[PDB]
Image (cartoon, rainbow, N blue to C red; front, side):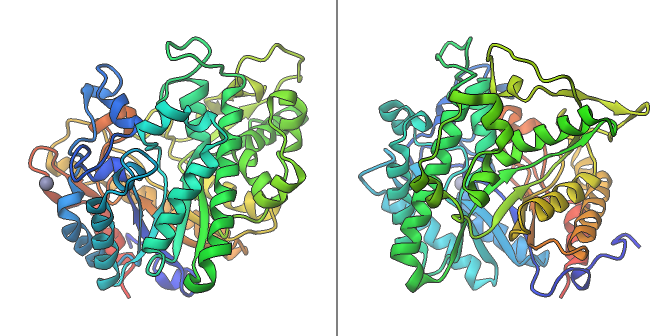
Length: 472
Ligand SMILES: [Zn+2]
């Protein structure tokens, strides 16, 4: 049968199933309703930055249609919805004056979710730094972000936390560091060669450190000021794609492990163990900031659960570790990506070139965190795949590859949970086709099709798969 034995009975009692969006990717009303610009507004409006020179001005217009979309997710038997609050919709300048119309939108959305029996899981940040803060403070390069983010978080806790009980601070800080400050392909477009300036060998590490310090500060504020009354939780969302040694050679096994450490360990060792991975300390040396004992103690234990965004897997080949002039976070890993093993690709690709369909990567990631980090509470906060541009409506709706994707990846998650992994929930990226960053509207990740001419929603086969799987 098309569920492949999956149902709510196949997962733990009270296991949470949801779908996911982010503010800039779905809301629209980017320069309306009092919202100030984010670094993504400025970036997307610059010709050449995004596929087709597209932007999130309108996106899916969830801002106007949110009750339609909530009705849809309830009809598909989901328990929860992960979405983000746009910082510049609340504070158009990132600090100071509150935009009451923005606050009203999130109140309305949260209230409707609760009315319809859908639990809100709310990200405070999803790439969309207020442009004013980038210009005034230099964004995540500035340690002052901890104070600025804490004050924003405090407002959100005060304003929404009597209703919202499941928070996340950041989303994929690794990708912000990598693409914003190593490769320079996401805002602020910084890198060694870049027009905007930068240094690919130092800035990614500064940025990651500031995300960690800012997360810890916001959680300390929650715990000391809001937790007694509100009794909720705050976590963080980290991407983790699996790395598998190309062979059982000492050097290939070491490479796959170095990659895991530079990818997920970069954040998880601080959050769980209060220090950066030893290999990062060894290889990155003085370019890796040092936590003071006090900071390390603030960061350690500061996530109530770990959100993992899990999409794909790669084979890794090793090499003798060399002394080399630093060039970039990416080059610091001293690993070699390889396409195939024993003449076979690791998996077929979805629309996105980086997205290899490798269901066993889900098991790899979850088992790895279980075994290495004392089995922390994990929530799979994103998992999904994309279709290309230019298909017909019917072609989008018959998304048999995505049905197969969810059945296979969820079977692998189930395998890890049945082996004892403390996974509390799973969220599909995305509820809706939406604005996919550099790919704009050319990448379709939704279980629900959105016609970007008419803005109409139509559930795809994968949406009905979830509805069947999740029936109560
Ligand atoms: Zn509208």
